[PDB]
Image (cartoon, rainbow, N blue to C red):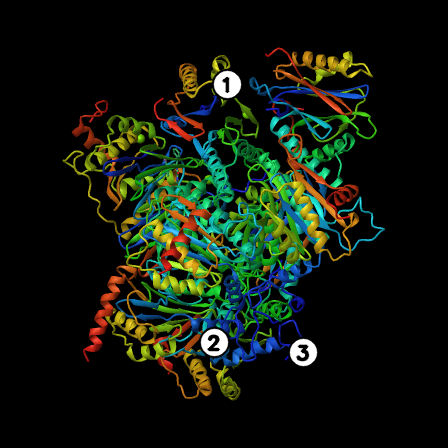
Amino acid sequence: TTTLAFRFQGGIIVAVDSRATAGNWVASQTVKKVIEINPFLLGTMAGGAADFQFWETWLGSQCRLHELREKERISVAAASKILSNLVYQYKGAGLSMGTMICGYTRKEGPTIYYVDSDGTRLKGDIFCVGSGQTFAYGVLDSNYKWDLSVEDALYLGKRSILAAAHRDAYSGGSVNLYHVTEDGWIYHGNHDVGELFWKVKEEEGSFNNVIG
Amino acid sequence: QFNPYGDNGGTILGIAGEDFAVLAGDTRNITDYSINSRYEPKVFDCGDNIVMSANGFAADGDALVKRFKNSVKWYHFDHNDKKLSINSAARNIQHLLYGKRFFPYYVHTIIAGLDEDGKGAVYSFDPVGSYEREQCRAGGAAASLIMPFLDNQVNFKNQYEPGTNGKVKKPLKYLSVEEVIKLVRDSFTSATERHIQVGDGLEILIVTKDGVRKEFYELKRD
Amino acid sequence: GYDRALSIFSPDGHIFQVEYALEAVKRGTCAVGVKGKNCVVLGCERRSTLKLQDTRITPSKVSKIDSHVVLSFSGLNADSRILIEKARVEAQSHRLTLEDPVTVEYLTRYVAGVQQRYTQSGGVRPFGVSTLIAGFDPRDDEPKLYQTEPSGIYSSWSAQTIGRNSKTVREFLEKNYDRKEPPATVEECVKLTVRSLLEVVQTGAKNIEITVVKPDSDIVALSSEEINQYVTQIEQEKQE
Amino acid sequence: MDIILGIRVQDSVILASSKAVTRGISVLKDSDDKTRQLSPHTLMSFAGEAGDTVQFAEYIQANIQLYSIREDYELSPQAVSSFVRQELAKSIRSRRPYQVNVLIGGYDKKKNKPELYQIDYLGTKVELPYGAHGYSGFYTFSLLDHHYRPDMTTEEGLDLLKLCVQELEKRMPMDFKGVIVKIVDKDGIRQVDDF
Amino acid sequence: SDPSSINGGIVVAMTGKDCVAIACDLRLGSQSLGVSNKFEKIFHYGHVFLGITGLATDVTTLNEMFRYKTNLYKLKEERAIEPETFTQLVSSSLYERRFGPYFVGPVVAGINSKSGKPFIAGFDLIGCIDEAKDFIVSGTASDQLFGMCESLYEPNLEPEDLFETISQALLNAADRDALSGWGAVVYIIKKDEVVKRYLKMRQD
Amino acid sequence: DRGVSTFSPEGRLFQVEYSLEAIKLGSTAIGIATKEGVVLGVEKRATSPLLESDSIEKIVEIDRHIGCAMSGLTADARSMIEHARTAAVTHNLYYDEDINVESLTQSVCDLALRFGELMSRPFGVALLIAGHDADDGYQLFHAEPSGTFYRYNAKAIGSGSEGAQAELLNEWHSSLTLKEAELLVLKILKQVMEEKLDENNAQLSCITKQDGFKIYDNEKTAELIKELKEKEAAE
Amino acid sequence: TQQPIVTGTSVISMKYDNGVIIAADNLGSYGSLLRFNGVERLIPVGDNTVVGISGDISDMQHIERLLKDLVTENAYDNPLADAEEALEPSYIFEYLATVMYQRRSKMNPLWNAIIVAGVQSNGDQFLRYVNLLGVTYSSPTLATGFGAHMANPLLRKVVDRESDIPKTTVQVAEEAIVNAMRVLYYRDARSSRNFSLAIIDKNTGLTFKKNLQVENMKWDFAKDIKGYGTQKI
Amino acid sequence: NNYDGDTVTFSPTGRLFQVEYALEAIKQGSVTVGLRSNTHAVLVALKRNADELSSYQKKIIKCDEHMGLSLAGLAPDARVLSNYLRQQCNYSSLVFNRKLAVERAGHLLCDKAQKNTQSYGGRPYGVGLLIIGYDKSGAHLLEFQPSGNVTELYGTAIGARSQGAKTYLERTLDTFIKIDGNPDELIKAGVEAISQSLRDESLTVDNLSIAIVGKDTPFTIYDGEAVAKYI
Amino acid sequence: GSRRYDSRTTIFSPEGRLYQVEYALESISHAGTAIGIMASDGIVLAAERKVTSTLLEQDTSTEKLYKLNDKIAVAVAGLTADAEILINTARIHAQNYLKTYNEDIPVEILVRRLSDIKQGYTQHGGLRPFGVSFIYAGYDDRYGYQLYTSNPSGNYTGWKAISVGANTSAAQTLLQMDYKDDMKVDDAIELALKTLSKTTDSSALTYDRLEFATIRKGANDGEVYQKIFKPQEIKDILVKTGIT
Ligand SMILES: *[B]([O])([O])[C]([C][C]([C])[C])[N]C(=O)[C]([C]C1=[C][C]=[C][C]=[C]1)[N]C(=O)C1=[C]N=[C][C]=N1
Ligand SMILES: [Mg+2]
Ligand SMILES: [Mg+2]
Ligand SMILES: [Mg+2]
């Protein structure tokens, strides 16, 4: 798995891969690793999990209940902490998940929270989680700036997943992009890696190692 | 030490058509190197035009199906005989499975039916409740033999159009119920040849707007 | 456990135990709340039947629930401590999970909910307490003032009074408080609060307590001399 | 392997704490503040097992803040440290203990004295002139043994602290991405933004 | 791993003529690392003295617990607890945690206020009472202390002679133990005066 | 004294019948169901002019497709709303769909008779539960503390209920528009209210399939009050 | 979790045209020790069902009491207890199957493999298997333990599929069972010569045969077998 | 009088007044009729409305594919009892793969209602039920009273003015019992029976509620234009 | 059932009073008078034993003045048995606080805890309240010398001088008259005894009918000493002040 999320001028980019494996067996190439929690909050998945389907769908119910009770959109900090406090109760019980709770509110601005099955909860600008995280970090760190256009930022996220999808055996399938403003998240296409690779290779002049 | 789990073998397959859906599964039940039954039904009609199969450990599989059938019944009581939609059934099953997260139903669950727009729908689950709608899914022992074939022959993966040489893909033309059954039968005939836990018989349940229909085919008994 | 249904309906559709809890509030010392343009003031009566008291250590009528919210009350003193403690815990619990202090509305809603629960729980009687909860929401300069009562109903008030002779001071506030133009400054708001208490209190010596709450956790309690200056100024203008 | 350090000087307590957060193979963050303000004149730094650390620190924080509101009074550093120790001493015999080591640096406004307390996850409290948790002490204590005086100024304490961090940066295998330094004195708690 | 030797430390107690002496080192460590040279292991409740070796968190916890219990004892009984009675209280308290014990080696010492009789006692971690006439030893250098005490001790020593004996018993035992030392304290206890002496010893 | 769950010689539960008397004392609430939507309206009834009337929350959102108005001991409604909101969201979690308005109402009404010697007494509040679902369309339910719920085309509860219900008897027809219904609620509220009806002491709300449940602004309601006055003066 | 102590070996069974046959030897083994030679492991319930049990004997005796108690309970307030509302094989099986699965789910299994053979109200043959894991399956032939490996192959030569059931008479079916029991005696080291056999026929009802013995055994050829290869004498 | 304060108290003549007051709640409730033949069993219920704007309170509840009841009295109590029946019918299926006998279903209701009449604090159920079903011993009709008394009958009626329908059935006993293999004629007899309990009001399309179960007929409810055939 | 015999101890009167609290206070009004007087340099606790006998062993007797810890003491007015239940609870709370924070419990915190316990019996549980009123005399380093009182309602208040039990109206008037803020312990001792001497229902005030105690900083350097007066010491202070 490779999932990333980074803050920038235009809000937040979220990019994930699509592969799920059971050992060396490729189970699915079509996995949605972004739970659309509500219209304003996004959550990612990684780690031999899908525990996070249940719990981030559950989180969406808690966030809905919050804004019914408080007549106000839940903060990214409050939403992330409901999840982190929940998984902390279950600490010790099972396997290894990792997530990024992403959102944009008035009081906070664009915010990303790395929540973890060990109970860790970190606010930050850039995060990469999954077996292919190191590959994604490489592309992201060298090309990241705050002053990135929405177009360029989307591409960087797409390219960072592609980099990991290529090298990491347990990442691949396709890239799901999301862009987050406070008006809501915006979906930006499902991009097959099989087609995206040859497209990027040719246009960018990258991947000269590979023959095409 | 007592081991509460077991492998009853078998293999299942769900394919979603344009206005139909099929859920197939072999009728062989096994432990280790012995055959328990040559005909032990594995795919069940659960009502509301939904078919289900929980392949793997038969005791957990039979328990889960039983509990879902029960869930359908109580859905009718509690909500004025409302028809349980396939998407709602899928989410309900997630909660049944995850309800035993720390002592799982050791099964690979697949349900098939029609969505609320009338189009074919197949949902696939893991043992701990994660699910996803899919056009094509094989589950169980011989899933590794069947899925690559389905990627090739249903979704036309790695296939391109002659003359263009890799430039233009093969178009994703829809498959008829007769065409799907041919792929199902060939999948199980091939799986039977190379997997010892697959054989005896193949039972297919076809779901259309008209209802649920059954088809049975012999498989090699060795 | 003791399960007896103490709060129950009567033929005429009344829960007498809730209504008798209001009678306990009627007996309690007067408490008043007035919100200005950029502040809220909480006035409280101290009955002068009790002298030889130690005012340093005697429980003050106004209680801080958090650094930005305060709670005064009329009714049974012992009962108020139970509501205050619960409210203070919930305030810290809210900060811990939501990572943001309670709104004055939320804190009020919680306290009111506790009070309500005691009107239909077995083996318990209702709280003989009405509260005035005041403060400023986090990162907000709009003043907030809420009232609660034993039944569990709550609501917001431009100005409000509870306790003994609250009918009289509510009469005063209703004619003297203008919504279109509330007390612009701290002085004007405190003055109006003291004036309203002087309709009931008796002597303006140690019988009036005033607590001024301002935005951004700026809460201060006025001393005897500071209050006595308001009392002097009010009566000197009155002699005309 | 997080490094958290503490030094009590004449009129203040200084707590240094690493900025790195490592989740296995990658450094996920290089600007993490491993501390919580328990009260205006009491600061607790912490290091231990992921999740447990913050969960514990915030739980303690909430309790001290609850006490402060109830009594309208700030607890002494000694009192807070004793409370914290009891929580960890209670924790160690629980089903799942808090795996958290802490330093509590506070300025006692009554006695007008800085106070540094070192408490490990077992609930082992010690009042010290300078303290550390984990492998941090192994490098730093030899420097602190040599250079430390009880009458040092805050600026002298920071210089001695720099010498400790430099030695850690030289000889420790893990890159801890520098430290966030905080000073606790009569005027409260402030952060040294340049270090 | 072994809780009783993580922090390290020692306590020794002796009887003399109309007096008792109890002594301890000052080290607290995290295995090899020395953490504190001011960790005193001898506490007192009225005229009853209690030394505690072993896991430091439990040393602290038990001191706080026996302070708690002896204070309530005093309020109700309207008198200070005696060494014989306290010994029983320690044993009771320890045994109630039979299958989840405090990892400690307590040592009671003191003089009975009424009879004037010198008293010492030692315990294992689960409450067994060792009420010796001559001496009690506890901690990571207990073997060493046993060797010193068994050779150096003689009965009916005067307070100022007893001090020299117990001091040398502790010091030389602590120097043959890696996890003990870093200073030492000796309490000389008489019926109505108690002298506390800090010893100068090697700091390694 | 006497049991809480005691039957009268007539065959009624004393405590349930006494709670109905408490609801008669409560402020008026009116609900009207149409094919274009359901309208909910309430009398706020502030006990003093110093009470900020906008804080009086007698109309409440349960979900996006279900709204609720109350009358009687409104403090008792809070736990009923919390349960209703939880029930609505919980069902969405289990079944990935909106919950039927009847099923929601049934879930609320199950609480009603959970009293004995569970809570110590019945609820002292009646609820008008209005909503929409795909199966039965726009619906209005009247939930009582007896555990009984009736569906209605139009319903009035509170102090001016029998007078308003008689007015709803004549005025309601199956071809009412949403705008007509809004005015009809305002008309009947103005008729039964002690004080003069305006945008501050009365509140409107509706539930439509498109926009979901909405509480009306005081500026929006003020225009509907002004529109009402003119159309009554028109003949 | 436990281990089985006193154990019962194979239970074999098959369907035939008018009903079902089930058989099991009368041995209660204590490891390699053939401890108890008079143990009945076929337990009839009513006049239309026979439950055959293998595995732990103490757990068998528990199951035996549950079935005995089931009949008692069914008779309570049931005027049709010996008629329309009498216990069916399907009812008795599903009950056991519920218990077996519940017990495995509490990690405290009844250490058994059970075969419920019987005939339903409508004359249909009932034959279904359940074990310590709660695993259930039905087949024209069912067998437990060694029976699975040796009996089934022989019984499947008679009834290989569903369509062979009406073609199989009670005489042919019983013969196959009795032969299978002999084969198990040759080859199962924890079996006995003595066994019980039960026939549940839709016409002639329940026939329960006790004290049967394996006969017509072939051993004579043993005399000719000498040494393990090269030895002649 | 002095002995009606709670359910735990006998009167001097050996009466349980709280039970009798609960019995009174049934008589206030709307009329409902039950009757059966050898093949089918039918419930006919007169639904009651609050006013013209209101709906008509549902009277019939389904318990299983082969069993269900009609209520008269406190509807929530019927919901509690019907829910219990649903679970018992369901327990029988899941555990024993067996459809619950109608007679045994009555025995379970009897015992559940009884516990409420002998214990302090609680109260009797304030509803009467007519349970119909088709099991292995053919068609059945039961009458449940909240005293605990359950009675198997050919036909009966409960609720207000139910005596008229009950007399009619007592005359028609020999006729309607013979209506085998004809659901419509059996319903006709039930509709004609409930008509004997009507005054002023008559059977309209949204007023009438009919249910039926039989040999090859699952328990199914008919409301609205589905019962216009029988008016 | 059992409802028939339930007194319903935790309910409001129509006037909004707690019946049982009011009646418990009526019980306390018949109890021996206890007085507390706080001075700048210490606190006095004086209390009258109720109609004693010559055969009562006074030197080993304790019905009025109890010690909660080294810094805090209480005077009792009401049922002695009820008071001892609360006293033991209070003693434990002080020790719990000490164990937790390693500091002696602040006086107000201890008072609030006991007062909260009394409050609990007036609101829930269906039990009768404790027929006890306390005078808390104590010291801590925050507020210094403090006097409090609690009653069965669970309400507590701070005082400079206060009486509980019998003739509190008469007693409170006399204290209000002669009390001044700059007063000292020796003067407060005299005031306490003079007040009891005038309000007593006995013919004459004697040593055998009194319990007496002082909390003084009159201890060697910065620390506090509790002095529970012995019978002979009460006799001496009665002669010194000129009452006998
Ligand atoms: B990713 O590789 O971490 C991925 C994320 C998951 C949410 C789909 N995990 C998996 O694919 C895991 C295996 C795994 C591989 C590498 C690292 C960690 C875990 N597989 C599954 O979660 C899985 C497998 N089969 C069916 C369902 N789920
Ligand atoms: Mg790859
Ligand atoms: Mg083979
Ligand atoms: Mg330590």
| Residue on which disc 3 sits | H11
Looking at the rendered structure, the secondary structure element under dot 1 is loop
On what subunit does the disc labeled 1 rest? D
| Residue H40, label in figure | 2
Task: Say if residue A8 shows up in the picture.
Answer: yes
Mark nearer the viewer, 3 or 2:
3
User: In what quadrant of the picture does the N terminus of chain I appear?
Assistant: bottom right
**How much space separates mark 2 and mark 1, taking CA atoms?**
100 Å
Determine whether H203 is above or below A55 in the image.
below
Q: Residue, x 58% and y 44% (percent of image)?
A: I181
Crowd band around label 1 with a 10 angstrom C-alpha radius: few (<14), some (14–19), many (20+): few
Determine whether H206 is above or below G169 in the image.
below
Looking at the rendered structure, the secondary structure element under dot 3 is loop
Looking at the rendered structure, the secondary structure element under dot 2 is strand
Crowd band around label 3 with a 10 angstrom C-alpha radius: few (<14), some (14–19), many (20+): few
On what subunit does the disc labeled 3 rest? H
| Residue on which disc 1 sits | D150
